[PDB]
Image (cartoon, rainbow over all chains, first blue to last red; front, side, top):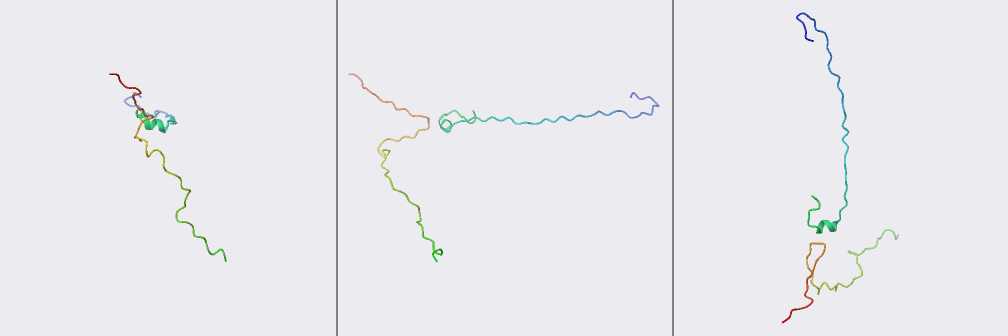
Length: 48
Length: 48
């Protein structure tokens, strides 16, 4: 306002508010690894 | 009158018996944790 000394300050606005919906999809990958490799391939294939 | 008696089955079901002589008795078995195994032989000998 910059309200005066004797002003009788009326109503003022209050901000309109928007909601945005993040959909939160998933992201999935599925490699196929073999049991002969995982038993015999001394590098840790699981954490690799 | 025949319904009220059921035949007695065997206690463990059985199979045709087969031989276990398998050459693993005489060959050299080794414990291996790899995709393969190597053996290293001397196909010749030295000189004097």
